[PDB]
Image (tube, rainbow, N blue to C red):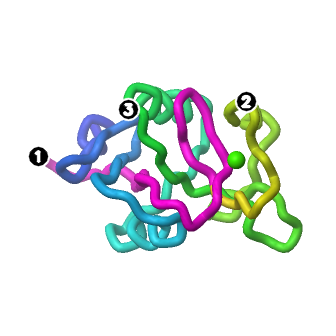
Amino acid sequence: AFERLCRHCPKDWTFFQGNCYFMSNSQRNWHDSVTACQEVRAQLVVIKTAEEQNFLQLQTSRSNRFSWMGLSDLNQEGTWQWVDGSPLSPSFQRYWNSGEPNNSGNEDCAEFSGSGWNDNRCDVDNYWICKKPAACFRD
Ligand SMILES: [Ca+2]
């Protein structure tokens, strides 16, 4: 019975597989999107599974919106790393759109666009997506 009581999300957030997702109503740059999610006790979305990627990408592909995710190459090595410190894994490289990542022109931040991901300049104003765990409590 406990699973059924562990699906609580804030209003205007979407539940998927144990987490809650917020799609913003306005646009900010990448770093300000990181901070926006922190302010609501969440994180600019870090994708952990293919199923999660498919869920998120489907919301994007319908919308024609560009949305920041919690992924950048902002480190000494210049490697793609999620904001929780985890590296971008080999099996997720299939999610970049054709032509991406450019890995040039300081396109250091990742965004959802269409059926996949782009790298883009971090000063661009995009929508953003936050993720936080769903809450467990009685009803
Ligand atoms: Ca790019």
Q: Amino acid at mark 3?
A: Ser
Disc 3 secondary structure class: helix
- Toward the front, the furthest residue is 105
Q: Is mark 2 within 8 Å of ligand 1?
A: no
Q: CA distance from mark 1 to mark 2?
A: 46 Å
Q: CA distance from mark 3 to mark 1?
A: 33 Å
The numbered mark, 1 or 2, whose residue comes first in the sequence reads 2
Q: Are marks 3 and 1 in contact (CB under 8 Å)?
A: no
- In percent of width and height, residue 5 lies at 24, 42
Instruction: Give the residues in magenta.
Output: 110-139
In the image, 134 versus 56, the foreground residue is: 56
Q: Amino acid at mark 1?
A: Asp
Q: Which residue is mark 2?
A: 98
- In percent of width and height, residue 44 lies at 49, 59
Q: Amino acid at mark 2?
A: Ser
Instruction: Say which mark, if any, is on residue 139.
Output: 1
104 magenta-colored? no
Q: Which residue is mark 3?
A: 63
Q: Which corner quadrant holds the N terminus?
A: top left
